[PDB]
Image (cartoon, coloured by chain):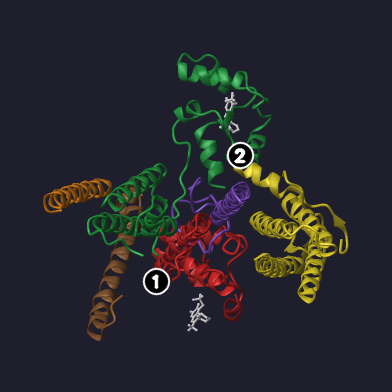
Chain colours: A red, B green, C purple, D orange, E yellow, F brown
């Protein structure tokens, strides 16, 4: 609009090509007008902040991708609360966790005894389904 | 990220380097012009013609390294914001209630808490009782769970005062 | 027991749950707004400068 | 600190530009 | 010549019709507490079939200003009224084109109306925070057709200006 | 812009070189600002047991 309203940006392809050069960091045909230069300065710092944010957000998600490994011990079970855990509803395993003396396993038995809903299953295949 | 006030210093240094570029380029008797020098300084600040005066080019190069350091630190600090996302609390101590006035706070309408805050001698708690006694609207709640629901429906705009054991119990439910 | 172990909150233990939100548009909305403001300001400046140039050309002839 | 090194380089290049323009003006006034 | 003017006229007519369809219904879609469609005025659920005005703006001050702008979709309504005014100006300049400068002002108002409609689309996308309605894509297509129609209009204007400059010499 | 073979290959050697250098500078500064926003100091005895 403005370049044909006051050249080398007279065509639609030259205007779109300078718009692409403004959208990326690098660039081609340098305008000489006041209004065209201020349109470039508005759009160009705009997309510079956008691609800087894209770089930072991709760096953040790749930082997330290299974070803490999954659960490897009962201390890792005590350290989290998102992924649930349970035993069979009847057997010597429940007697072992019930009569335990370690406070970590005591907190495990307290959480599995006060969970909503029940984490206990009837059979082994029911636990496989769960 | 990186600043709340330093951007104005960046813009003022941009104007100053533009004035220096116009002083070098337009005092030698092609790259002259105050707006041409300003737009070349704009092209120096972001990424994407060059003067041949061999003295203001040093100014352009140091400004160009300067804004490269700027955008490197900008990318770094914005990644630092987007990495951890550590939400912080605006209110920490009891003096934070007297320090501001946007977020309100209240007690129960009747009880020994009101007798404590009413018969106080500390000027901080006296100002607290003055603010809670002339509050608009009525900040006092009917019951305890009504005050809990009033805080839960406040979206960070209203607080309730009570004993520590009950508050630590409600925090753990 | 009756506050932390009986309670249903596992607070101060978990920490970060990776924050799996990509990016909201709230970080982009004011940037769009200042883009539109700059475009409209450039439109009005270009129109008044063209009107002033046309008036000067009509007065000079 | 980056402001400080920018102002230092700016003032250094400004004084260098001033002395080279003064020497060029003196040489042009002496020769021509 | 006249074929490009007729193409610009039917492009402005199609852009006005798609803007009317975007104002009408099915602008957005969202799952309530089953999905539900919305057309920036009222929402209709998938009981199933009931419709009500769910565009309630209440339940910093810049958030209140953004909620006031997003209330009742003020910017796309003003953009559609400006597109109607630009279309009326283009229809008045098509027949008996006496002044050779009303087309440029009509095209400038048309491009500014497209920019305001894009700003209103950014506002309507900003207040959304799952699918989207087809009238949003229809409004985007009308924005693309309006951009192409503005390009064709200023191309015809610079062609007429070059013809007037060639005939004046 | 130069037009020679050898000058262009000198530029291509030096230029990707310093591009990788400033990319590493950006990444390392981002890493140290990530370190700067890490875990707060000790606030309880559980934090004493954690370290
Ligand atoms: O004496 C016992 N010997 C057991 C031997 C086994 C096996 F591993 F198959 F040999 C198992 N299972 C492990 C889990 O899946 C089902 C079968 C249970 C046993 N139980 C029941 P507990 O009381 O729960 O230990 C006993 O009582
Ligand atoms: O003797 C008293 N003992 C009190 C003991 C308690 C509790 F903590 F539950 F043990 C409470 N609550 C505090 C908040 O949760 C609801 C009830 C109020 C008490 N009050 C009323 P006050 O006069 O307002 O302190 C007394 O009078």
* Front-lying residue, F6 or B114: F6
Depth check, front residue: E97 or C17: E97
Relative to B140, residue E151 above or below: below
Q: Which structural element holds mark 1? A: loop
Residue B59 in the figure: left or right of residue B111 = left
Q: Position of residue A100 (x, y in %)?
A: 42, 62
Question: Residue A92: horizontal and vertical position, in percent?
Answer: 49, 72
Foreground of the two, A111 or A40 = A40
Q: Disc 2 is attached to a residue of which chain?
A: E
The N terminus of chain E - image quarter: bottom right
Mark 1 CB within 8 Å of ligand 1: no
User: Where is the C terminus of chain E found, in terms of image quarters?
Assistant: bottom right
Instruction: Point out which mark residue B124 bears.
Output: none
Quarter of the rendering containing residue A128: bottom right
- The relative height of residue E74 versus residue E159 in the rendered view (above or below) is above
Task: Evaluate whether label 1 is on the same chain as label 2.
Answer: no
**Residue E130 seen by the camera:** no
Q: Is residue E76 visible?
A: yes
For disc 1, the neighbor class at 10 Å (few under 14, some 14 to 19, many from 20) is few
Disc 1 is attached to a residue of which chain?
A
Instruction: Say left or right for B161 vs E66.
Output: left
Residue E6 point in image, percent of width and height: 81, 72
As helix, strand or loop, the secondary structure at mark 2 comes to: helix
Of residue A55 and residue F51, the one placed in the foreground of this image is A55
Question: Which residue is denoted by mark 2 in the rendering?
Answer: E61
Q: Quadrant of ligand 2?
A: top right
Q: Which residue is mark 1?
A: A72
Seen in the image, is E70 located left or right of residue E50? left
**Residues at marks 1 and 2, CA–CA distance in whole angstroms:** 49 Å
Label 2 crowd (10 A; few <14 / some 14-19 / many >=20): few
């Amino acid at each position: 609009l403005v370049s044909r309203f006051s050249s080398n940006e007279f065509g639609i392809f030259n205007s779109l090509w300078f718009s692409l050069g403004a959208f990326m960091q690098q660039g081609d045909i340098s305008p000489r007008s006041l209004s065209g230069r201020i349109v470039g300065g508005v759009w160009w710092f705009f997309t510079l902040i956008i691609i800087s944010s894209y770089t930072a957000n991709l760096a953040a998600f790749l930082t997330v991708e290299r974070m803490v490994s999954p659960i490897e011990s009962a201390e890792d079970l005590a350290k989290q609360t998102e992924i649930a855990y349970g035993t069979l509803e009847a057997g010597s395993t429940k007697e072992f966790f019930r009569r335990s003396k370690i406070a970590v396993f005591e907190k495990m038995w307290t959480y599995m005894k006060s969970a909503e809903p029940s984490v206990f299953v009837r059979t082994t295949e029911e636990g496989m389904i769960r | 990220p990186l600043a709340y006030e330093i951007w104005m210093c960046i813009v003022f240094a941009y104007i100053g380097v533009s004035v220096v570029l116009f002083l070098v380029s337009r005092f030698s008797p092609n790259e002259f012009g105050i707006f041409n020098s300003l737009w070349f300084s704009l092209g120096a600040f972001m990424r994407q013609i060059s003067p041949r005066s061999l003295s203001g080019r040093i100014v352009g190069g140091v400004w160009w390294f300067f804004t490269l350091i700027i955008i490197s630190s900008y990318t770094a600090n914005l990644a630092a914001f987007l990495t951890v996302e550590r939400m912080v609390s605006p209110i920490e101590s009891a003096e934070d209630l007297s320090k501001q006035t946007e977020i309100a706070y209240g007690t129960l309408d009747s009880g020994s808490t009101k007798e404590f805050f009413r018969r106080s001698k500390i000027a901080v708690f006296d100002k607290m009782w003055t603010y809670m006694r002339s509050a608009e609207p009525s900040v006092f709640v009917r019951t305890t769970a009504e005050g809990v629901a009033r805080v839960r429906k406040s979206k960070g705009k209203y607080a309730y005062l009570l004993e520590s054991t009950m508050n630590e119990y409600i925090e753990q439910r | 027991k009756w506050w932390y172990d009986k309670g249903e909150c596992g607070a101060k233990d978990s920490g970060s749950k990776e924050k799996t939100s990509a990016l909201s548009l709230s970080n982009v909305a004011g940037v769009f707004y200042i883009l539109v403001g700059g475009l409209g300001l450039a439109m009005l400046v270009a129109l008044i400068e063209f009107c002033y140039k046309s008036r000067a050309e009509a007065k000079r002839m | 600190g980056v402001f400080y090194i920018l102002i230092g380089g700016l003032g250094l290049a400004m004084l260098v530009a001033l002395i080279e323009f003064c020497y060029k003006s003196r040489s042009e006034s002496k020769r021509m | 010549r006249g074929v490009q003017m007729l193409l610009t006229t039917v492009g402005a007519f199609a852009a006005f019709s798609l803007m009317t369809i975007a104002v009408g219904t099915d602008y957005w879609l969202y799952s309530r507490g089953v999905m539900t469609h919305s057309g920036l005025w009222r929402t209709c659920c998938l009981f199933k079939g009931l419709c009500k005005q769910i565009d309630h703006f209440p339940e910093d001050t810049a958030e209140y200003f953004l909620r006031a702008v997003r209330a009742s979709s003020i910017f796309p309504i003003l953009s559609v009224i400006l597109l109607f005014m630009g279309g009326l100006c283009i229809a008045a300049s098509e027949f008996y084109k006496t002044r050779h400068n009303i087309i440029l002002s009509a095209g400038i108002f048309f491009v500014s109306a497209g920019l305001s409609n894009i700003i209103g689309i950014i506002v309507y996308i900003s207040a959304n925070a799952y699918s989207y309605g087809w009238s949003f894509y229809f409004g985007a297509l009308s924005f693309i057709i309006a951009e192409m129609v503005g390009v064709l209009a200023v191309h015809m204007f610079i062609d007429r200006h070059k013809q007037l400059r060639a005939t004046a010499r």
